[PDB]
Image (cartoon, rainbow over all chains, first blue to last red; front, side):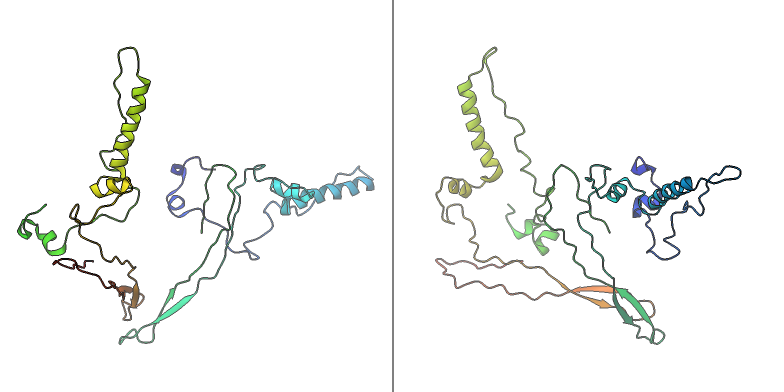
Length: 144
Length: 144
């Protein structure tokens, strides 16, 4: 929530924010506040089995939310409904491309560099956005 | 309007005159003397709406001229007429070619140059003038 580009720090402002590593077991853990146990109160000597039933149901709603419905839009999708991008002010994703960056090695050829190599990665790529209709004034930003 | 090659300065005489950068917003501005307002006198308390009408018309001729008819030949074209190249003594353009100059990179291969590159631009090109009839003695100059 920085208010001005001037509230950003050296690195961020010049290179952009940092993003998440590709997903793996250690970089895609369940949200840190994930419940590991759900307590349910009980009268000194008895337990309301009907309440216990509700308790679970309630928990279920809580979990679903924590695990994958943390964003309003996703909760509404949960019900089988939908939301315009104006509903939560989300930028509209118009096109997403992804590709691997490969290249070649350069062979060292002098007395000491003979048998050495330097990797030069150089990948060509196309990123094409199909004719899009702009309903209101604004910006079309493309990032990498 | 230099009179003799000897009136030219070091750089010009050896390398040729300088030309305009490719056209862009900052290198193709409307001629510096472009009108930003056109005044029209008016009697102390009234304005001749008929004059105002003429005033605009007159302005229009002035603008058209400033914007794109600064050369005699272009004004005459404006009327849907034409002018020989002898009319304003303009050199006759016989052929105009244009192309991009690309090349390749040379890979550095020794201990310190390994992983370095040097751009060698080398472009082949054809410039062909179709059989032209020379009506009077003169010169056929080709420049780049």
